[PDB]
Amino acid sequence: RPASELLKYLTT
Amino acid sequence: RPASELLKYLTT
Amino acid sequence: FVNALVSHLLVVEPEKLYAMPDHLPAVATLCDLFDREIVVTISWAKSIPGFSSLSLSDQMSVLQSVWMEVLVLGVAQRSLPLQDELAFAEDLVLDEEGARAAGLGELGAALLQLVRRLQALRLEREEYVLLKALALANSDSVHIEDAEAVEQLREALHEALLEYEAGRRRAGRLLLTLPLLRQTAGKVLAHFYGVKLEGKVPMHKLFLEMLEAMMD
Amino acid sequence: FVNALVSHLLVVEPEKLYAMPDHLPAVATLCDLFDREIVVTISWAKSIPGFSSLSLSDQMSVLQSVWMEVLVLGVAQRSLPLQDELAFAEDLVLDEEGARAAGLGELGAALLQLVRRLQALRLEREEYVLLKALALANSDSVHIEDAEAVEQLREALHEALLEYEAGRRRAGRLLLTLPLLRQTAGKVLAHFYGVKLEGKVPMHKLFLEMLEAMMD
Ligand SMILES: CC(=O)c1ccc(Oc2ccc(O)c(C(C)(C)C)c2)cc1
Ligand SMILES: CC(=O)c1ccc(Oc2ccc(O)c(C(C)(C)C)c2)cc1
């Protein structure tokens, strides 16, 4: 499980 | 239960 | 200059939160308000000078370790006027027993403890924003790749604070409150880790992700 | 003056510890060494300027909340020369796996984390003693009676540090390490709270007393 919801926001 | 071992040292 | 940073910290701050407004943030329900606050924190961190020039991983290592501090210090900030009470939003004011009822446990006491401590300083807008970005840089995570880069960002913000504490001993006094912030944040996390394990109270995506990132 | 405090902090410091000496402290065995360290901490606190003129309860409220920090920062201090290793005494040097074996759990990692952080500062004898008495004053305990008296002792030591950091930004840099100290101390305590509950590993009077004083 990668940090999916966190990745979203940090790369949006 | 009072702080027995602690009381000792703080009052010795 | 250093106020160019401060005034950018003022600009980048999340807008005053309200549970039930009416042009600010939309309008929530209950705990989705907290979910929203993770999101607001994350986007804030991006906007911190020095931050977005870390690697993507270190940005995540940093966030995953201190995100709850940043959040909690924010909630400390709102609760600054009120006594014996917790300003969740401007709308939402909750006393110790108000907190237990909504399943926060002992957290009311914990959070008042931190509020008092910052109240004893009449902490300012500029000072708080400076300390929150400082809390952010003060991560402590064995997972950070560029040790120097975070330390330089740390030294930087502290110097930003020193150059500010002049327009004198107020730097450290603000800094001295930081240990309680981490401890308090840690009690918040540890609580919802119990909730996690109870598995009855349902939890939202990002919060579980943050929770899970921590133990392993 | 302020160095009259510093030189009294230097004087009052616990002597260099050794597990197996040979005129310093007697000679222990294994974990009794830790028990001894609680005792050393307690007597130290008495000797801190400002402390013994608190009420007996506030002295206990202070000690029961931060005693493990003071201890751990001490052990951080010894481990300062060594890399990737924990200086329990001068005699006792323990790496990460050395720590697991003696039932410290994940604590090796935790404690190196703090060591590194202080190493990145080449922290001085005078500076450390100043920060340890400062950690002591920085209690945070809802049980304290005279809120002002502790705060005045806090402001005092920090000023003592500022007047010292001149013979400049090193005050805060030292202060910035404190949140990790509390967190680290807290992991140490939380660990031995599990041990407590397992009830198999036997524990000594004072340590259980300190452990029990905390939850309730
Ligand atoms: C189970 C669940 O997801 C959840 C339940 C309650 C909750 O309430 C809170 C709301 C805002 C807020 O800022 C805080 C503190 C950070 C003060 C704890 C708590 C948050 C999350
Ligand atoms: C069950 C028991 O009583 C106990 C077990 C191990 C132990 O080992 C230690 C010795 C010194 C020391 O400073 C520390 C740390 C504070 C680093 C954890 C641990 C101490 C106490």
Image (cartoon, coloured by chain):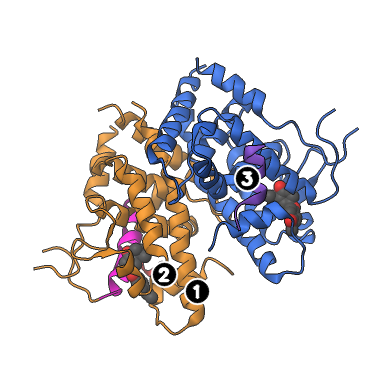
Chain colours: A red, B purple, C orange, D blue
> Do the numbered discs 3 and 1 sit on residues whose CB atoms are within 8 Å?
no
Residue C105: which disc?
Answer: 2
Nearer the observer, C42 or C55:
C42
Helix, strand or loop status at disc 3: helix
The vertical placement of D214 against D88, above or below, is below
Residue D71 spot, x, y in % from top left: 64, 43
Residue at image location 72% in from the left, 54% down from the top: D205
- Indicate left or right for C29 with D170 as reference: left
Q: Quadrant of ligand 1?
A: bottom left
Residue C117 spot, x, y in % from top left: 36, 46
User: Of tags 2 and 3, which is closer to the observer?
Assistant: 3
Q: Which residue is mark 1?
A: C194
Residue B7: which disc?
Answer: 3
- Tell whether position C90 is magenta: no
Q: Residues within 10 Å of mark 3 (few under 14, many from 20)?
A: some
Residue A10 visible in the current orientation: no
**How far is the residue under mark 3 from the one under mark 1?**
34 Å
- Indicate left or right for A9 with D12 as reference: left
Residue C113 visible in the current orientation: yes
Residue at image location 40% in from the left, 82% down from the top: C202
Question: Magenta segment, which residues?
Answer: C30-47
The vertical placement of C10 against C39, above or below, is above
